[PDB]
Image (tube, rainbow over the protein chains, first blue to last red):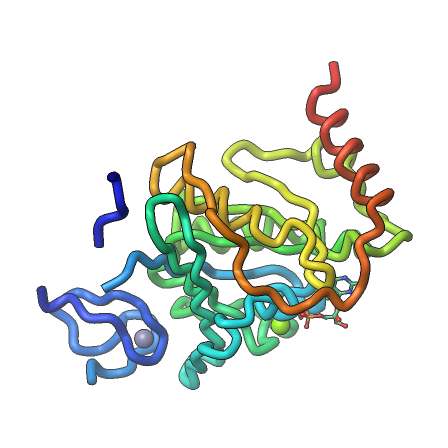
Length: 34
Length: 202
Ligand SMILES: Nc1nc2c(ncn2[C@@H]2O[C@H](COP(=O)(O)OP(=O)(O)O)[C@@H](O)[C@H]2O)c(=O)[nH]1
Ligand SMILES: [Mg+2]
Ligand SMILES: [Zn+2]
């Protein structure tokens, strides 16, 4: 099967954007990593 | 964690963006409000032959009626839908402006163009006009949010581009709010015919 494939990278709890481990604020909505 | 894409849904006010995204029942019940940007993010799951895909659709709170949207709305957008109203020519005329804004902050993300409200007899923007101004890399679909007509097609096209798999399929339709108006099959057959002839015309 070729099922779609999915480390400090975090999904914003507010807007769901995936953010780099280097940042602590969401690059899109500026809320802070929980 | 899951396969998901940020999808920005843009277009003039009153074209049906909110009505359209809301057809996906689970995406509505699980939507998330971003207070800092005035956005409702709808997580829309679609089940493909290779597993589930989530389009996190960013829906405005009407701010588009008064000016441009802030950069945060577009940041990390991986795909987009540009919507206009077939019963209002000005919404089509503004399509290139939305396109420009998207490419400024997002560049060559896959984009689908949707002409909404095709359930209305008195259509004004017709297949001839849209196919004459067809732009490469910009797939188009007729849609009717209130009737669920062609609801899945923008998302299927985007999923194929994003995954890079021309043979991706949805194995089942998502649970959609029951149609509030009927899409007359005759109009559907006509608009579909008008679109095919206009695309294969010599
Ligand atoms: N007949 C018909 N009416 C629609 C459709 N979509 C929206 N409408 C109406 O267009 C008006 C604006 O809808 P809305 O979703 O708020 O557009 P938005 O401002 O872009 O979010 C509303 O009165 C809708 O009921 C459609 O697909 N068919
Ligand atoms: Mg709206
Ligand atoms: Zn965020």
